[PDB]
Length: 46
Length: 46
Image (cartoon, rainbow over all chains, first blue to last red; front, top):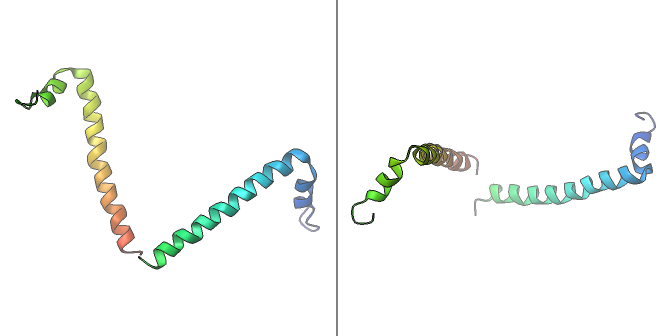
């Protein structure tokens, strides 16, 4: 797993767990976008 | 109730509802303090 990177492919391979981890990832992208906006409001008060 | 200011005392009279509103009041002063602290932290971070 750790030498070959076959952990993430091990995850990608199964139908159920692909949907689970993909769902968690898209949610992750949107959260990080919101975080970039929030940091922006802090760097410039107005 | 509105002329005598006796609405608040009317609530004070029943014990169960008095314990209820007392719980709500203590939660209030604590909230306003935390709000001031959050505003302060915002002032000294950006």
